[PDB]
Image: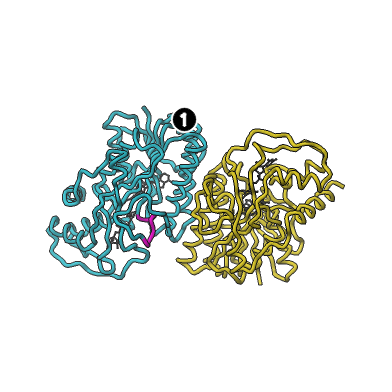
Chain colours: A yellow, B cyan
Amino acid sequence: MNILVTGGAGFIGSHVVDKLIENGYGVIVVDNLSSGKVENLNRNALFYEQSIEDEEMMERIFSLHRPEYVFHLAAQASVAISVREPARDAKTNIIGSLVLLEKSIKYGVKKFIFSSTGGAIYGENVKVFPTPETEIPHPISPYGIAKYSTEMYLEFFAREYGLKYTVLRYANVYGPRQDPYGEAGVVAIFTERMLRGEEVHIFGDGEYVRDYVYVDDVVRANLLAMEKGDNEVFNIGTGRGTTVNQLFKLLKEITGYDKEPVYKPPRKGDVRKSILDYTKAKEKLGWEPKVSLEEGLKLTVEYFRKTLE
Amino acid sequence: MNILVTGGAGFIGSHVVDKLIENGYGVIVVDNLSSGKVENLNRNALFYEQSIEDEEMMERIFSLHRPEYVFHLAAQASVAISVREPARDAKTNIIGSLVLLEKSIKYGVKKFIFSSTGGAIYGENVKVFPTPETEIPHPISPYGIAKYSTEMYLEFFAREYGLKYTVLRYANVYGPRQDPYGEAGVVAIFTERMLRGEEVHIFGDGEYVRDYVYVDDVVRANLLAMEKGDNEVFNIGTGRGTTVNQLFKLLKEITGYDKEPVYKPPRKGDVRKSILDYTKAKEKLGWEPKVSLEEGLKLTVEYFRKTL
Ligand SMILES: NC(=O)c1ccc[n+]([C@@H]2O[C@H](COP(=O)([O-])OP(=O)(O)OC[C@H]3O[C@@H](n4cnc5c(N)ncnc54)[C@H](O)[C@@H]3O)[C@@H](O)[C@H]2O)c1
Ligand SMILES: NC(=O)c1ccc[n+]([C@@H]2O[C@H](COP(=O)([O-])OP(=O)(O)OC[C@H]3O[C@@H](n4cnc5c(N)ncnc54)[C@H](O)[C@@H]3O)[C@@H](O)[C@H]2O)c1
Ligand SMILES: O=c1ccn([C@@H]2O[C@H](COP(=O)(O)OP(=O)(O)O[C@H]3O[C@H](CO)[C@@H](O)[C@H](O)[C@H]3O)[C@@H](O)[C@H]2O)c(=O)[nH]1
Ligand SMILES: O=c1ccn([C@@H]2O[C@H](COP(=O)(O)OP(=O)(O)O[C@H]3O[C@H](CO)[C@@H](O)[C@H](O)[C@H]3O)[C@@H](O)[C@H]2O)c(=O)[nH]1
């Protein structure tokens, strides 16, 4: 069976590729290496260094390999970049998705499994925590609007053509291969700076709450979505909130870092609190996180240590 | 004062241009003539035959003319077509809007007035009519999804840069210069068929209810949104529902058409009923329709007779 993984050279996508390869699937990867890395690629997967919004190239790849599933992880994944360049962001995030969906219909894809976002979708005025999928989306960033627009297009493709899909709205994903450089998640930034004994910055008062979910658990969610959760949207998170202050403390203890954090002005656009309810994923996908935050942070620090040897 | 009107060679946009010119504004028009027509263009406007999604070209236009207001009417504005090539549709409908908004932010535009849609945004299970802006959006067509995505981006630009905007969600717009040969626009199709004595087709049972709003009234709402209704979404419609069968009868009486309609199979995706509550526009824009349907249909027939 052939499987297409877009964004397979990236943080989450490369782990998805590895797992599919391990389970015996034929895997085809599309990635333009805008943020992904050649080192992340699996030598057993077929690789196309190409862009998802390239209609002729996507036409060619789908016609050759007729993937039965598409795992769509390719995205402009930085919120800050989406703010600075919203048209370019939407070209990858919306138009890119629509090209893949057009080819998926044309070439008989059975199911499209889309990586979406929990944090950038529910908006800034949520009152129910942990937050369920029944909360109406109010995205405020271009990234969140693009992800939400694409989820709506998925429902269109299901209604019009009978394409099955699953949307996975991730919380804050962290772990090995997350890039600590550029537009990085705080786990990777903190871990790398602490190991190097560099200064660590906390924005605003550090009381921002997030739901940190380990990359291996997110990969398992993707695989469970192959045969379950048809035409459903799921939060993929832990339902546990952690402030940036608490996170710094955990990582400081693990790394043996011995400096205080430097408090900096608050970051524009930061939602105050994000925690996801995963009851639905538990009931319909049989999904639950297996790696606690403390276990996950230790694994993460361990991977980064090896990079520094 | 300079004003940019995108889609200014189209049905609604050409009338907006006319009204601005009449009121003494300098008007720049951007239209790629994908569905618009040179014959619609006001010769007093400065015309760029260019595409809104062209960043380099929009850079030049905004940099040169520094428009104070943008009336954004350019769209792949037809619901069929959006279904078969949604990526191409979203390139005009979403990416195009985003390019205009980036340039708007960069070159100090004061207000952006966006043409959106009522019907295709509220979706197919509405229970309250006439329908207020508080009704939760559930667009299921690529056209409605794209329009709604753009509305959401407009709020981002307002929050991030202080750009002021107004969204006008039109009902079913009809009147002079609506193209009777395109995908849609039942009023223009019926009028052209009837005046030519050709067959007239009613899809399904003809009991589909729409809210027909005259183009000159839609133009007045655009102009009222220059100074009022900052950062608000408004339904622009009449609050009155008309079946296709009723529309047929009205236009048959006006044209003197002497045939019965030919019924065809129902058209896939047609919502059963769309009627918009315009109370919010009435209060905040001071807007109301000045042209009743009967009066507007007569003006439309009047115009079509002259034009073919
Ligand atoms: N905490 C998180 O990391 C998080 C949270 C919520 C959602 N997500 C989503 O999960 C997916 C993967 O995220 P990630 O953390 O691994 O980021 P990532 O940057 O590491 O992976 C994205 C990959 O997509 C590639 N890419 C970007 N544009 C492309 C294009 N036009 N054509 C082909 N490839 C392109 C990049 O090169 C990159 O390898 C994304 O959809 C992202 O939005 C991630
Ligand atoms: N007519 C209605 O009943 C109705 C109802 C709801 C919303 N609207 C909206 O009002 C606006 C105008 O509608 P209309 O009836 O006048 O349609 P229209 O097709 O006559 O006008 C659209 C104009 O935009 C131009 N255009 C399309 N793509 C372009 C691009 N990429 N770059 C530059 N120009 C481009 C077309 O050439 C055309 O002249 C649209 O946004 C439409 O979606 C119309
Ligand atoms: O050096 C740093 C970096 C981050 N933060 C704080 O850490 C928190 C989390 O930031 P970040 O790691 O950037 O996560 P989010 O901004 O929440 O982004 C998450 O949410 C995005 C939008 O939902 C996802 O989709 C992203 O991939 C995901 O990492 C925020 O409060 C930041 O203020 C710091 O204090 N110091
Ligand atoms: O020959 C025809 C043509 C249309 N209809 C019917 O007329 C009604 C109105 O159709 P149409 O004129 O195509 O408009 P709509 O489909 O309602 O709606 C669109 O009107 C504009 C396009 O014409 C869109 O952009 C607006 O968003 C949306 O209101 C529908 O019930 C059709 O079934 C007929 O019966 N016979």
Residue B143 seen anywhere in this rendered image of the structure: no
Camera-nearest residue between A292 and A109: A292
> In the image, what residue type sits under mark 1?
Gly
Camera-nearest residue between B262 and B147: B147
Q: Is residue B121 magenta?
A: yes
Which residue does the image show at 47% across and 62% down from the upper left? A156
Please report the bounds of the magenta region as a residue range. B119-125
Q: Label 1: chain?
A: B
Res B190 → quadrant: bottom left
Residue lying at the far right in this picture: please name it.
A309
x, y percentage for residue B282? Answer: 28, 42
Residue A31 seen anywhere in this rendered image of the structure: yes
Q: Is residue B7 magenta?
A: no
Which residue does the image show at 57% across and 57% down from the upper left? A56
x, y percentage for residue A268? Answer: 59, 37
x, y percentage for residue B123? Answer: 39, 58
B32 left or right of B39 in image: right
Ligand 4 in which quarter: bottom left
Above or below residue A82? Residue A104 is below
Above or below residue B239? Residue B45 is above
Residue that carries the numbered disc 1 in the rendered image = B108
